[PDB]
Amino acid sequence: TDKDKLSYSIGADLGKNFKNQGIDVNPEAMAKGMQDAMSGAQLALTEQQMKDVLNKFQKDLMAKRTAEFNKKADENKVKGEAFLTENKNKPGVVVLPSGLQYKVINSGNGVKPGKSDTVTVEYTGRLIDGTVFDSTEKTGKPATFQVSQVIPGWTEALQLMPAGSTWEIYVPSGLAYGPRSVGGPIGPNETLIFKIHLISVKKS
Amino acid sequence: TDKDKLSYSIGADLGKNFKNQGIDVNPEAMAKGMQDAMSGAQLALTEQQMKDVLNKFQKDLMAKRTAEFNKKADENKVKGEAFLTENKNKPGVVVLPSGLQYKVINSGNGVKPGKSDTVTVEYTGRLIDGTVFDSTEKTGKPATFQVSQVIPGWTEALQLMPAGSTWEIYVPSGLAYGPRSVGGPIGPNETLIFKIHLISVKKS
Ligand SMILES: [Zn+2]
Ligand SMILES: [Zn+2]
Ligand SMILES: [Zn+2]
Ligand SMILES: [Zn+2]
Image 1 (spheres, each protein chain N blue to C red):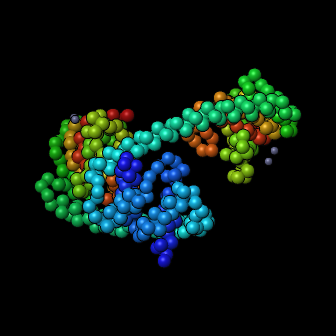
Image 2 (tube, chains in turn red, green; image 1 turned 90 degrees about the horizontal axis):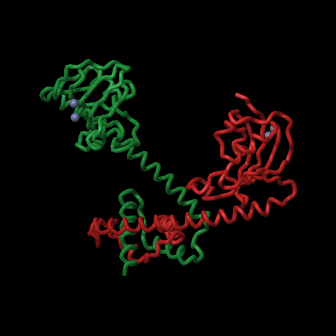
Image 3 (cartoon, rainbow over the protein chains, first blue to last red; image 1 turned 45 degrees about the vertical axis):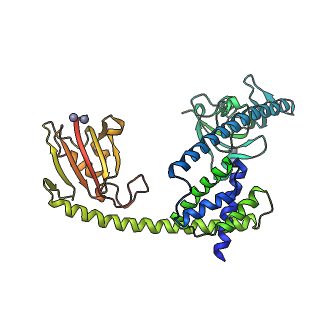
């Protein structure tokens, strides 16, 4: 029946998650507790008891995540440097003192923005694996930022770009979000790629 | 074993939650999905399929919450008015045009704050059932607010209180948080009680 239908779905949903993480269990004793709970029956474990163990489960989960995080970080830095080394050679790529690299898609003729100016742009940011994490295409509307409020790579690139230009920049993690990053698709020590079209400079 | 131990705890934890809410299920088909998932076996339902039904489960959950919310709201207003009606009589209670009620614990002799002044106070806010939702006792440190940035009942009361006084105010929901309130311990149309000690007035 409709009941039977959903129940499976929820558990299928749940069960995957656990596994994918690190929750090594036995759905038999686990199915047991569920029935106790719903039947409002007396629980095989003291409120305290459970909490005591759950509290230890999370603490150990936290340890696990931190493990992955620090491992991902070391991994992405390694991948990040391989990408840039590989890219340094590619046709049209210029490498700057800061390690920031760019390739000119189309050169503009307007003024280059200063450190304090406001800029209007259109862009798409992607990870080395093509995954798009941000872009003005979705919103269909250009973005406006103050040159100094953006990530270092952008700050470094914009000061070199004539208004009207379209560059593709390749950003070392130290010039993007760095070792930290419990944010969106961007992880720790992730090197990023951006296609940036600088529309105009507001020397405000 | 240690495994068996935890598994139960998690499921006991989970199972309660569902029940307490409205998730009428059968932990048998639900235990089934969990095993499929972990064994990485082929799932009895198409990725789509499950989502299709889960998406419908939440939407129906949302309907359920909204149900409770609106019901709680009508309930708390009724309780709120019974409390104030009962309280209007009690020794020392003054009822104001706005329905706000207060009782003077101890009268100060300083100046009464104006609408724009900053005030320094110590206080404890509780629901009609004694549940404390806020207080400066916990932090051990007085709070400072601008008379107009606080809830109406407070704004109404403070303008009447001589600096140094300690009043207990009984606040109609329309002068506290009103019909809205997906916040802390405070729900919809909840009438509140406060013990407020006005320490000083900064006629800033
Ligand atoms: Zn365009
Ligand atoms: Zn353009
Ligand atoms: Zn005190
Ligand atoms: Zn005092």
